[PDB]
Amino acid sequence: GLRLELPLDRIVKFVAVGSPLLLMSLAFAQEFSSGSPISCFSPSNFSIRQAAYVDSSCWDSLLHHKKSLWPHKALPYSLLALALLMYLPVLLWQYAAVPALSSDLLFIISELDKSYNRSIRLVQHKERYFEFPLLERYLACKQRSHSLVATYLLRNSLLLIFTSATYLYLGHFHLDVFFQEEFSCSIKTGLLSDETHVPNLITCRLTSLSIFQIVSLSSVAIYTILVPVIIYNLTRLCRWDKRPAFDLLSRKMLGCPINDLNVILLFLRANISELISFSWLSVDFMTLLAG
Amino acid sequence: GLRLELPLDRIVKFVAVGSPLLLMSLAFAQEFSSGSPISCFSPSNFSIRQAAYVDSSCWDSLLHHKKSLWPHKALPYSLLALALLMYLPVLLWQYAAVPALSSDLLFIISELDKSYNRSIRLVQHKERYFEFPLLERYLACKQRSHSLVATYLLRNSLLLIFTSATYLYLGHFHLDVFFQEEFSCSIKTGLLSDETHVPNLITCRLTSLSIFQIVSLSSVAIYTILVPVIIYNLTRLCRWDKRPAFDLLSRKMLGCPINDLNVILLFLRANISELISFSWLSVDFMTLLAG
Amino acid sequence: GLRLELPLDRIVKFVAVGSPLLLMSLAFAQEFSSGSPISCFSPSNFSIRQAAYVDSSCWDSLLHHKKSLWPHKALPYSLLALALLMYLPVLLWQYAAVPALSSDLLFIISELDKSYNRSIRLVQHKERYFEFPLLERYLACKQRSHSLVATYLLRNSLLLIFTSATYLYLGHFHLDVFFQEEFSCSIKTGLLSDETHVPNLITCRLTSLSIFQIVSLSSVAIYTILVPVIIYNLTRLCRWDKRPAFDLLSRKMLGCPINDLNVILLFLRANISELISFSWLSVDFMTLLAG
Amino acid sequence: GLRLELPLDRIVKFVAVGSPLLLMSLAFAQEFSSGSPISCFSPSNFSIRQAAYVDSSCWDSLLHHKKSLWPHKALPYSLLALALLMYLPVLLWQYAAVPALSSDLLFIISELDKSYNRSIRLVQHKERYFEFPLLERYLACKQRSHSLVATYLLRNSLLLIFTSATYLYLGHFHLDVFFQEEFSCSIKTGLLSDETHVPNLITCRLTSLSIFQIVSLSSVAIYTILVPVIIYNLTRLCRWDKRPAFDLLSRKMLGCPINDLNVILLFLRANISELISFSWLSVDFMTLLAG
Amino acid sequence: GLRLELPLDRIVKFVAVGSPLLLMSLAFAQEFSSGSPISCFSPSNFSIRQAAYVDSSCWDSLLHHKKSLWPHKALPYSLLALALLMYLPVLLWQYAAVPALSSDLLFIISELDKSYNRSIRLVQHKERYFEFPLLERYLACKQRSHSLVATYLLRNSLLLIFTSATYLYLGHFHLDVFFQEEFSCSIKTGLLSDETHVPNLITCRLTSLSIFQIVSLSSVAIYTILVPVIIYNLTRLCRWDKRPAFDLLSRKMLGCPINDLNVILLFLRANISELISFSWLSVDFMTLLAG
Amino acid sequence: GLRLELPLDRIVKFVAVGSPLLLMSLAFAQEFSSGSPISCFSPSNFSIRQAAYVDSSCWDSLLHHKKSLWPHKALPYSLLALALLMYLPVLLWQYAAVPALSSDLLFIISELDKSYNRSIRLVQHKERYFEFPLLERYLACKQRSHSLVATYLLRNSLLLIFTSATYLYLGHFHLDVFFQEEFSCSIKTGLLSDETHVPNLITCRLTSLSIFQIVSLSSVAIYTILVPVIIYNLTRLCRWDKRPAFDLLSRKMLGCPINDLNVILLFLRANISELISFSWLSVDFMTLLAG
Amino acid sequence: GLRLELPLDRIVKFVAVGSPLLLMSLAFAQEFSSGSPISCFSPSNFSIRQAAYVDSSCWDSLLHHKKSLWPHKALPYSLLALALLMYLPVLLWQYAAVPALSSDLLFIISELDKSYNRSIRLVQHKERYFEFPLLERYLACKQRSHSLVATYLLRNSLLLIFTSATYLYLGHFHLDVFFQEEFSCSIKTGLLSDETHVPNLITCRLTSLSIFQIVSLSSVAIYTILVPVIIYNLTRLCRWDKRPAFDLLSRKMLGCPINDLNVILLFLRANISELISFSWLSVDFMTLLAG
């Protein structure tokens, strides 16, 4: 029943994955309802099937003559790609960091409990500093590594990079097609030319500009909101974490803070409820700890 | 099986989250049924496709010429945003207050049970005042804090602020479009101008004014009803809570009532059924307590 | 596995909550099927879209000129409100009476079982009257209260009040629109006036008068049926309830019958199967009770 | 795991409740499919909307001029009412007879098992007649009552009464509208009069006469079949039921057969598998019973 | 975990009940899809609604003038009735034979196991013939009865009778309407007569003759296949069943084979896996049985 | 948790049953979508209903005049019949072979384990050849039988026969209608003759030739692939199976290989994981087997 | 609870199987929505049914005259075949390698645990090299085999081969039909010729070119991404795997690396968490291992 993810990262992943899916569903469920996502004012003597042909041709082309409006067609697929892009760092953390850290937390929790139990017999009263050789050798070995701190940094770095990519994509493509609801589509380009019945230019109107605007604005707003929490999570480990065995923990509590020790200390602090935290909530001393 | 939420707050959160979703579903399920949410009286010689083009264009524009009716289009999305705004304080309370308070309740419950068991042997008859040092040191440490009382106040403060925001939004936007069921829409503004067939102004009628009025009135009524219960919950802790170990509880029962002691006392009173409340329901005395 | 609700109240709540929902579903499921809930005999030269505009406008207005038929539009929503109005007393009883009464029943059941077990050793043969001080002090304390009897009365009072409100609403609004299946609707009131093509008055017919009549009659009938059972439940406690420990129960069996003793006695009688009711089904005596 | 209902009554209740629901579903699922349940031969120059108006008006009126065909409209609702009418006696038996009889069966089963166990020690060989005072006093008390036999009779009486009511309703209303598939409907009665375009009389045809005939015939047939089993169940207890402790049972096996003893004897016989029925299947004697 | 039904009867009941339901679903799911199950070649000047009226009238009448085609309309209901007719014998066997036979099998299995255990102590080496008085008295009592063999015969007899009824119905009604896909329907019989516009006779074509033919042929084929297995099951008990305690079984293995002994012997043989069948699979002898 | 089916036969049955169902669903789900499965080029002056009549008549007839195209109509039903034809051998194996073989495997497994346990005490060191009389008598009795080997052969024989039947049906019927997408249908054969308006011959086109071709080709390909695995399974037992107790197994390992011994040996080899296969994976010797 | 698949192969199989199904669903769900997947500009005097006939005929033919566009019709079926082609290697690995390897891992894990337990008693201080004869004989027997390494290589080889086949198919067929949205279809080839009304050539346009392009590009991209991980998995075993009993493991750690030893070593390393890995996470020595 161990908890292997910080509470903030859980809600960050949930929001970042869920929101593009919700926006994509809000766009799929409207164009199926309204029918065609584009209308065209065909001439009066175009019967019925020729009007449908004009509609389909202008929707397929999507090129304003008098310049290109391709983002309208590729909205839900581009939104769906964002879901996979957000889900990739979660998969990386799931399949690259949690197996080692799970064992590293279980072992340290068990031996911390054992050390507390051993110190209990000393409480009811110095062969204590050397009494835990494992807690010094193992912790010195892990402090010199750089194994999974890199993955923890890189997950947030990837999330920030993809957020910046979304910013660039939106601000470079969707901005130039705002407030553009109609365009002059043409079909007299290929073999249909040299045929006098069909007019030269046909006006057509997009029927889903509101969905486009709402999706763009909402996505920009939420992915703006989601940046400070990400940078806070990234910068959380930069400052040194401070709250018998805890004395030995504080003994090697110094130096550059970029190790594997900081992440396991953070996960230990976030999982303090597993071990006996009776004395943790009450922040002489031996008399109080006697009970 | 501990209960970590007051019964009143449960129903308040349930109502405040559920009702905008129900109203939004009552609006989605009608415009899909009736087809277009707006009709237009196109001229007789407009064939079929041109009438649909006029309908779609006037629905997209939604601007009365002879002034703007944008709330009609943005009703379900604005209602959906209210659901997230209501759900945010619940998330804050879930992820910021309940972990510490759960441990603080478990510890106090266990040691209260232990103290009652110890006093039982004294019942069947003064080393009793000093017999519980933890119940004095821990309770004095928590009484000097201000940790989670701020969150408890801020949840209700946020709910009140968002209710006021809903009031302002409704009374500033929806009021000026009541009793307005039809408008003169125009399409001869862009490239469609200088074309004599289409008339200058086309009358159009909204087919969902009843849903608009009903949703607005119902939402105003329910969020009016939900205010006194919120202010009662906020003001509940302002008055000091009054009902061996309970004597020590009453001993430090004084001073300014804004501490972390008041909230844990309220949760203890609301969870009296966990411990032995045999003597609680019967509100000399030692002879009665002997059984 | 305690039973905390009388069997009659269960079926009363089930009927009173379920029936408006069933009637509302019988009205939603028909107007979605038949299409428009109102038809209009537009002139022959009105094309197609103008007829739909006339239909929508007359349905939105719903005002007979040659007086108002608004109950037809607001039938399912008014029926849905009745469901919440019926559900409110159930919520009140669930969140205001059952927690105290559950403990009060558990304690009395356990101590009744203990007293029966103690009297068993006296059966196989006067320090018996004073042998149960708790059963006298606790029962005298509860007999002087007025705590949850008020809630039990007020639940049925609220149900009766809401039934009377439904009576008044139906008999004051739905009665004047019976046998009215068609009306002369007009659209030439606003900007559509001074336009000679549209006629002055257009006949329209309601296509759901049968559903209206059936719903009204059925609701009146069932809420007429549901009144005598409610008044019987309310008047049940007015008469004093009569069927070692039961001798002490009969000892304080007198006085004004409006206490908290009557309701707990009723719940004890309705939950006689929990304790040992071997002698209850066989209604000298010590010889029979020896087995 | 006690069985509290006779096998015949189970299938009777299942058939009587299920069949009207099945017939109602066979009528709902057809008129939604075919569209309108009535067609009308409007004149050729009635455009499109006027034909729909004529259809809806004639369906709402449903009055043959050259006399009333209201059963066609009220078929599924009248069938649905039969489901509740059939379900009411089941509810009465569930909430009025089974709680007392459950305890009365459990007690008699347990003490019968105890008596058999006591007689076992006498088998391996007269203080036996007086050895079971409870089996005589309790059984004499129950034989003088009339408590739940009245409910058992009244359930079948109510079922028979409602079957007779269904017979009367069908044979008094549905018989006069058989072989009537078309009628002359009129709409020129109210304000539509003094208008020369609409003809005086319009022929209309019912499109669901086959469903009407099939439902009527099937319901009559099944509720004819269901009567002899009901009367057999009612008359089952009139004849006295005949198959140490069973000798005492046979000792008071006489007199008028209308008591509470007959019903509990029937339920005991139908639940013979609960106790040790090893000797029941083998229908000197002590030597055989020794094993 | 006893098995109370022969494997062959299980598949027979499954096929006989499932197949009419499958055929009925294959007919419901096609006429809902294709729309109307009958088309009519109305004249050119019949507008739109008059053609629908002609279609509905000819479908309702279904009477060839120049003789009756009623089986086409009543196909799915007649197929549904066959499901209940097939299910009735299963209900009879479930509610009339299995309760007695279950106890009769449990008792004989337990005492057979006991006898085998007793003979085990004699194996490791004549007070054996009289050692099982119950196995002789009980088996002689059951051999003289005729209780449930009649039900076992009557179930298969009813299945055969209903198969013959299906044969007669199909071969007497469906045969005369094969290769008949169109007919001359008339509507000028009632009040529509003396009206010159509608022609005297209108040709109409059935659009579901293929479904009719396929259903008829398939049903005939499968219910032909299902007869030999039924007659084999019926004739199975006519021949005497042959494979310490089994010696006593063979001792009364003679006489007329129509008893209750044959059916319980068949069920014992079909449930040989319940008891110790170690020696059954190996079909001197005492030396082999020693292990 | 015994495994009673070879892994190859599992996938063979899964493929052979699933694939016709998948192909049938790929044909049902297309003709419901496209509407009519056949179109006809009716003349210009045929109104609307006469065109539908022509379509339905030509689809029902399906007879090219200038020869018969009946396989197009009977594709999904003929595909559905193949599912039952494939499922029949699985039912035969389930209800005719597995009950005897299950017991025969359980007994041999248990006694093999017992023999291994007995030989264990001899390992840690000739009364061993005669030490297992059952393993010789029972195995000699089963080797002389021919009971369930016939069923095992006949299942694969039936599968091969039905595959050959499918080959013959496809290659004899579907081959002559390939590359035939249109035909000249006629309706002027019966009473519609001697009527000048309808032309003599009407061209019609099949709209589902692609589905026909794809289904035919895919089915031929997969049932070609499925033949070598079937013949391998059939020929598997023809060669003698070769890998204290296993010495006795090898002792009677000779003669004609068509017995019941081969199938139980195959199932034993396929279920080697049930017993102790510690020495099986390591393929002097007594020293190695000591551990 | 053993893990029998490498984590990388799990995600590879998941992606390779899921993605063609997702792409196929993205193509099925669009052409059902838009209606026909192809439109045609029929002449004005073609009524309604002739236009539908032209549409269906041109969709069935799909042959540009002025060369063949068959990939458009066969997109979802060709995508569905890829799912089975990807699933086949997973089935091969499931039914050909995992049963032997499961036992081979269980045995080695159990005996490794036993050896560690035996060495524990030697830790707390040379009959150790010969102390594990099984770990040498069994491991030498498996090192000389080539049984399941071939299957492990062949699974990835098959995946690479099918990826190359997909590359060839796409680049040889889909490339020549890009940027081709319309074609000149003809119907005047068969019996419809010599008929002057229908024109010689009819222009038609594909309405699903965007789906075609998106599916092709996306599939190419993802199956390009999936190649380096496959080749990494294939090349993983080529390099020798390096990290009392582990000394014996290192003793035969040499030679050509193509054996069955490498795969079981890889699976042991990937399943290190099953056994006691307390000393694994802490990478003199005996003093540290004493705890």
Image (tube, coloured by chain):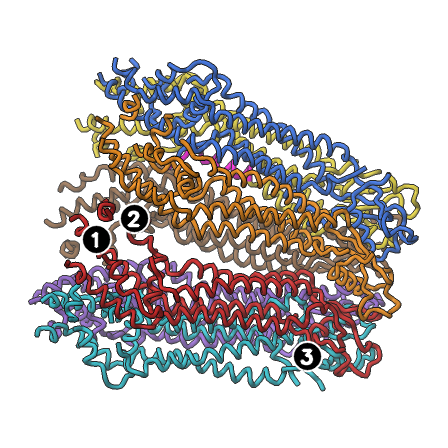
Chain colours: A red, B orange, C blue, D yellow, E brown, F purple, G cyan
Question: Which sits in the foreground, B219 or A243?
Answer: A243
What's the mark number on residue A117?
1
- Helix, strand, or loop for circle 1? helix
Please name the residue shown 44% across and 59% down the image.
A8
Instruction: Tell me which segment is drawn in magenta.
Output: D1-17
* Mark 3 lies on residue: G181
Which x, y percent locates residue A53? 74, 72
In the image, taking residue B11 as reference, residue C130 lies left or right, namely: left
Which chain's residue wears label 3? G
Please name the residue shown 14% across and 74% down the image.
G133
* Mark 2 lies on residue: A278
- Residue sticking out furthest to the left: F125
Which chain's residue wears label 1? A
Question: Which sits in the foreground, G41 or A249?
Answer: A249
Q: Residues within 10 Å of mark 3 (few under 14, many from 20)?
A: some
The mark closer to the camera, 3 or 2, is: 2
Disc 3 marks a residue whose amino acid type is Glu
Which x, y percent locates residue E8? 41, 54
